Length: 230
Length: 230
Ligand SMILES: Cc1ccc(NC(=O)c2ccc(CN3CCN(C)CC3)cc2)cc1Nc1nc(-c2nc(N)cc(N)n2)cs1
Ligand SMILES: Cc1ccc(NC(=O)c2ccc(CN3CCN(C)CC3)cc2)cc1Nc1nc(-c2nc(N)cc(N)n2)cs1
Ligand SMILES: O=c1ccn([C@@H]2O[C@H](COP(=O)(O)OP(=O)(O)O)[C@@H](O)[C@H]2O)c(=O)[nH]1
Ligand SMILES: O=c1ccn([C@@H]2O[C@H](COP(=O)(O)OP(=O)(O)O)[C@@H](O)[C@H]2O)c(=O)[nH]1
Ligand code: NA
Ligand code: NA
Image (cartoon, rainbow over all chains, first blue to last red; front, side):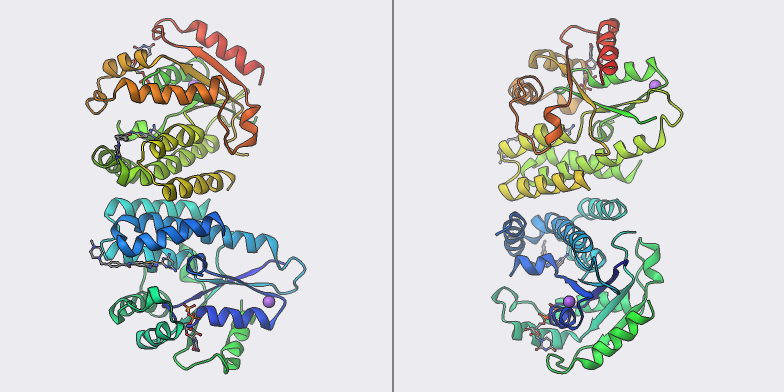
């Protein structure tokens, strides 16, 4: 019938990729849209482009943040629409789990880059204008959000575990900042956004500080009860 | 009924703004979409943004070309869709004259900036990918193109006439380059583009080297005969 759209949100290395790759397996009605940024740091023209801009961001984030964020968000919309138009056509209760959303792109990452002075006012205002417009022009509007909530310390341990060379320099302070934005947006709900419906949108919060790779039935029970109310 | 969409194309200072402001007056069925870049170098957030990026382009085109071209093209699409959805609702034979198009943005300006090394390969490929996609996601597809063809020398005289301080340093060589791209795209038709229908799309070419401010009936006769065949 009509696909239910659920964003999975959380700090770096909270366990979102682990979680979605568990969910996709448990039902034929369940599919996953991986974060294009994750696929760039694994050959498509999008991957060469993303690979090039990720690398240039390490050298000069104040040069490449605007270019990165716009291309990261474009790539997510096109990947979200491809899944929405290519899968779960003969599914009874189809659910599409997005690894993060257009809202994390803006109110977590792009916002953080503006606050770290990696975008100037003109770049941030062009970005927001582009984002408002790119999204208007109800299709990927979310039925619900699942917040995988983890302490910065757990996420720092899990970056160590994941063992990506590029990521081993991420400091606790950076994760503390991303953590703070997730708390304000999804838990305290103190964040003004420019998308009216988000304030209604149901949020399931899951504490994932404890390892769940081999012990996730309780999280899945809460997901199925969440899905039943939508 | 359904609005006919005609792009006016031509080098800087060929006379496109003069021409469209003549056409808009001759019929209630005739409307004009001015080039947003033209309105930035005349307060909306789009105008502050465009004003800021135009200024920064004079200092450092190799820093701002990507940002400029993407925002210039976004702004044109939104302005084209606003006219298409707000005017000529009770017009019998409605015609909408676009001052330039999404195709001039790409195959004239962005392309020229890439060739002048103001965009690197990653910026040019991101731009083209964005452009392909932004346009797909038949609405602003053109019924025809009117090429106001003028020599670089006429355009250089007309920049002098227009008397914008910012423009008085434009050299003949730059206009010769833009002229060459217009000839290849619209006259010789030697330019491959990534939009299949453009190769069919009818082109009216008008020699506008002679002043027409007070003597434009012949040009308008050719426009009305052109419109009749579409
Ligand atoms: C790959 C990479 C490389 C480098 C940096 N760098 C910085 O974040 C950074 C900022 C500031 C500073 C200090 N500061 C001093 C002052 N100068 C002027 C200016 C720099 C130093 C470093 C970040 C990344 N990763 C990023 N991924 C995203 C992202 N990830 C998604 N999954 C989705 C999405 N939409 N966005 C956003 S950022
Ligand atoms: C306002 C402004 C300011 C500056 C420049 N500058 C250069 O074009 C320029 C390039 C190259 C050079 C030398 N080159 C040496 C080598 N370094 C590395 C790199 C620079 C020097 C200068 C152009 C403009 N105007 C522009 N308007 C458009 C445009 N106009 C529309 N109407 C629609 C649309 N889509 N685009 C495109 S460009
Ligand atoms: O309960 C968990 C969740 C995650 N991980 C590991 O933590 C790292 C980060 O998780 P993931 O890549 O899923 O994080 P994301 O960035 O996708 O949130 C990976 O090496 C996982 O295998 C783990 O050991 N136990
Ligand atoms: O037949 C003409 C056409 C144009 N102009 C002048 O040439 C300049 C450039 O024309 P316009 O601004 O229309 O050029 P565009 O950039 O819009 O092609 C302006 O000062 C016009 O008044 C003119 O004197 N005679
Ligand atoms: Na599945
Ligand atoms: Na009119």
